[PDB]
Length: 209
Length: 209
Ligand SMILES: Nc1ncnc2c1ncn2[C@@H]1O[C@H](COP(=O)(O)OP(=O)(O)O)[C@@H](O)[C@H]1O
Ligand SMILES: Nc1ncnc2c1ncn2[C@@H]1O[C@H](COP(=O)(O)OP(=O)(O)O)[C@@H](O)[C@H]1O
Ligand SMILES: Cc1cn([C@H]2CC[C@@H](COP(=O)(O)O)O2)c(=O)[nH]c1=O
Ligand SMILES: Cc1cn([C@H]2CC[C@@H](COP(=O)(O)O)O2)c(=O)[nH]c1=O
Ligand SMILES: [Mg+2]
Ligand SMILES: [Mg+2]
Ligand SMILES: [Mg+2]
Image 1 (cartoon, rainbow over the protein chains, first blue to last red):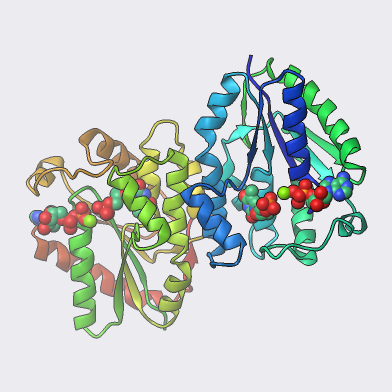
Image 2: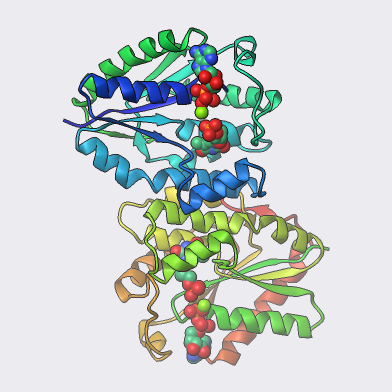
């Protein structure tokens, strides 16, 4: 009985990392086998180049860095497929949707070109999009010092996310991330339990194909 | 007056490297400004990962490595465009066509998926394909010890190259690489002089778009 592939995506300070950690903890306390993953996975050779870029310690050509972000997901595909086939549910903090939205926010990058490197990846069984209003996010502290952490760029990324959500091939679920950590967690947890039951019924899909 | 972008592609031991070096030398001796490039460009961070993979010193997931090879070309795009705009002709030993043919030779890799990361690269003004028969290549020594250096895989790559040559958007020229080094060089040199004259007349194109 395979595990489910659950992805969390969402606006800045929406709570992707907090909610991914709390979801894995709750699923395991409820008897599931679940594990956390994140992208970028900064531990690999590729992930180190990506972390340096995001920290502004290095500059990388925009197409090259887009392809590195995708390559960073493909290097984990053998692990992802092994874990799911062994019955482990994977909760993933960011995936291909962030890859497309962030590069797609830059000038002269079509959504089509951005998606192609990730075509074929393991298709999530559930994509949670944590929605939040700029005013409510502002109360979660200040902007980071990493690349892309500015209002005008986040807004362009958000528009790209909305284009991606028009894709009905995917099981998108909107989450009101403005509530408390615990309330948001309960909404995500219940959606996740339903997805896990259902993932055991259809084979793992392929993204965007 | 921009320089031309000339790519050499071709079967193993066809003479891509020898002919790229001899072409740059001859063009410069004839008063042109010309410089040599090669892919993979093993000197960058990405190129080191690719060289290690080809040497079998490391294993890389097939999609990830395909994307690294493309990222390795995009990191050189700013340099390529600057040089061409300054009137320097660039002679390139392998380009996106090798990227597609080699990954396309593997199982379950469509030509379409393989091409996408390189869509948009600087479009060559001339693509020379150095053709050679297995018998004639065998006389050029033995196979290398790098990945992909075996008959069955080279044959699959060759079929992919033939699919790519059906693309009429590109200025493909077949070269009979079975002749002497000097005879093959003269054929390439004359084709290259004609391309250089003509490249000053139309803007640099975009590959596969
Ligand atoms: N529902 C929430 N309400 C208030 N603050 C929150 C909420 N979720 C997360 N936070 C806080 O906001 C900050 C960003 O949360 P984080 O989970 O790191 O978001 P993301 O990974 O989406 O950037 C952290 O300080 C976190 O504790
Ligand atoms: N026309 C030719 N005839 C005979 N040997 C050749 C010819 N062109 C190259 N060679 C030899 O074959 C080998 C492979 O040439 P090389 O230029 O490195 O090919 P490639 O880069 O296509 O693998 C080298 O030893 C080279 O000297
Ligand atoms: C997964 C991914 C992410 N990004 C950006 C957005 C946020 C930042 C990671 O920041 P966080 O570590 O705070 O999640 O990196 C991309 O540009 N492309 C990708 O493929
Ligand atoms: C440019 C390129 C090349 N290759 C393979 C073919 C040959 C080898 C380089 O060998 P040579 O150094 O001997 O040219 O690497 C790919 O798989 N993808 C690419 O994008
Ligand atoms: Mg986070
Ligand atoms: Mg060579
Ligand atoms: Mg397409």
